[PDB]
Image 1 (cartoon, helix red, strand yellow):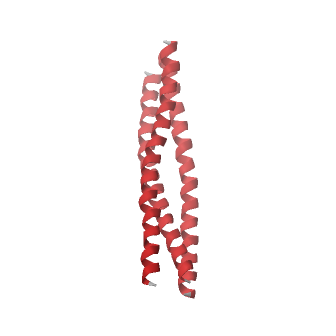
Image 2 (cartoon, each protein chain N blue to C red):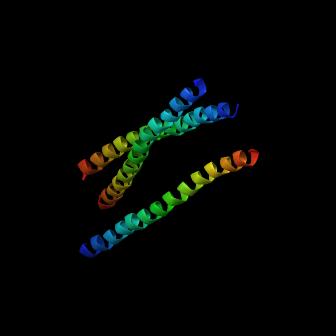
Length: 49
Length: 49
Length: 49
């Protein structure tokens, strides 16, 4: 029961950590997309200048 | 005996997920600084325009 | 100026449409690599049993 109880807690940590990792991964993709759009504006603004 | 190996595997998975999650935080900080620097560069280029 | 601006917009669309297609295909490729790591561990565990 000690290892079984501790195993359930360890498994729950993976699920809890996976939830935060999913949001972090999605935020990284969203932030990366904004960097691409910002880079295009810099090149377009610099080219227009 | 076999259950002990499963508990160690679950605990090790938390370290692997935590390591990958911790790495995402470092990349998120870089994107935040790059986004802030890109905004300043765009403002300077737009202001100079 | 209108022709250059219109022609320049075509290159901008290619940098986003083609990039999104490569990013979508690249995302699926990275998922297969992670699945290969999990499958490799199952072979060592299944072979031991």
